[PDB]
Amino acid sequence: APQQINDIVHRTITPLIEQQKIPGMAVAVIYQGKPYYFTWGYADIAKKQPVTQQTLFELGSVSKTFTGVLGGDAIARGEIKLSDPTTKYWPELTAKQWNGITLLHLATYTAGGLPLQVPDEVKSSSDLLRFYQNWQPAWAPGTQRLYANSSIGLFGALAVKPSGLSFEQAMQTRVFQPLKLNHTWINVPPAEEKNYAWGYREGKAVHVSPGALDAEAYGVKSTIEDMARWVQSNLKPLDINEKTLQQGIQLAQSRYWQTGDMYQGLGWEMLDWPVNPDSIINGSDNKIALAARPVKAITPPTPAVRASWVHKTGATGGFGSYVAFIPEKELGIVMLANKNYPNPARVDAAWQILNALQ
Ligand SMILES: [Cl-]
Ligand SMILES: [Zn+2]
């Protein structure tokens, strides 16, 4: 890699690892469209297995960017419209509070207070219907954003219904395979477990446990190389030969809602570039990121703005991930760690690197 990239990465990430006690980490810096890879530490501490460019990490909510793009691909196929009512795809949701709640609301966390988590007691299809049938909104739809797995998670499950495919099969055939993400998994196969890093929570090795709508909301595992390719695909949609996927990527970076200086995409979140770094750092703190905030609609949605900071944080019990990129500059970063450490530290490190290379 160029000397300037090696220097800033060492001076930014090695101290981050020192400060946050991260056992293993993989970083890709995309510079002038090309990825440069860095690894530190261990995928499995007790086995002394190093992090490599083939190590799988839990992406947590970075999974939502895949869900948003898969939804965008469905829009471009004419299979769904974001204005469609939820009940078009789930007629059994007869409770009156669902009148007026569209796929747009589900995708962008604006249905009116759907909760952050689907409750752990939901283990069956009927449990899930009961949950949504009895949920009472705190706000009218399209007025408040409340980040929620139960919102975008349901969006993903319904967006694939017209195709007749399962969510996992739709994602594999329509997103992973065309983009040659051949080491990206909703369910890690037995032959790849050897590359599945352990996450570490309070010194204990952990993996994410099954939950309702997990594949849609937080269930993808991937390598640093496949995640660099995901960033390249989102930086350069016109290089994707499948038109519906090219358009799906673009639609996921459309701006549908604004609150403060932040815009909500489909999975992705965006700000205008140049960005105020303190706003992305401070806004990544869960005290803000998980809070209810009024939104203003953008009608029609703004088509993907190349001068944007586009990003997403993700966490599981044992992992912490961050992706950010700037289409106008062909500049991006992927940070995958097997400890869940605070989002503001992730964003600050990412901005120090990309700011140095702009
Ligand atoms: Cl140094
Ligand atoms: Zn040093």
Image (cartoon, rainbow, N blue to C red):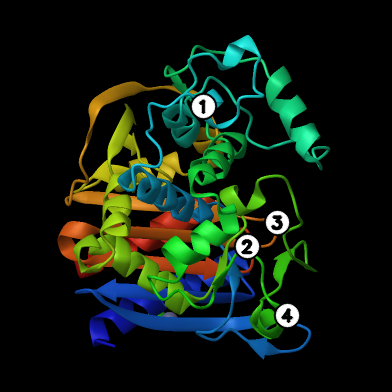
Percent x, y of residue 64: 50, 50
| Tag 3 and tag 1, C-beta contact below 8 Å | no
Q: Which residue bears the numbered disc 1?
A: 88
| Tag 3 and tag 2, C-beta contact below 8 Å | yes
For numbered disc 3, what is the local secondary structure? Answer: loop
Mark 2 vs ligand 2: CB below 8 Å: no
Q: How far apart are the two marked residues, 2 and 4, measured between alpha carbons?
A: 21 Å
Q: Amino acid at mark 3?
A: Gly
- Which is more toward the observer, 286 or 98? 98
Q: Along the polypeptide, which appears first: circle 1 or circle 4?
A: 1
For numbered disc 2, what is the local secondary structure? Answer: loop
Residue found 43% across the figure and 61% down from its top: 174
Residue found 67% across the figure and 24% down from its top: 92
- Which is more toward the observer, 97 or 94? 94
The residue mark sitting in front, 1 or 4, is 1
Q: Which image quarter has ligand 2?
A: bottom left
Q: Amino acid at mark 4?
A: Pro
Callout 4: few (<14), some (14-19), or many (20+) C-alpha neighbours within 10 Å?
A: few
Q: Which mark is residue 190?
A: 4
Q: How far apart are the two marked residues, 4 and 3, measured between alpha carbons?
A: 22 Å
Callout 3: few (<14), some (14-19), or many (20+) C-alpha neighbours within 10 Å?
A: some
Q: Amino acid at mark 1?
A: Lys
Quarter residue 257 falls in:
top left
The residue mark sitting in front, 2 or 1, is 1
- Which is more toward the observer, 104 or 328? 104
Q: Amino acid at mark 2?
A: Phe
Q: Which residue bears the numbered disc 2?
A: 319
| Tag 2 and tag 4, C-beta contact below 8 Å | no
Q: Along the polypeptide, which appears first: circle 3 or circle 1?
A: 1
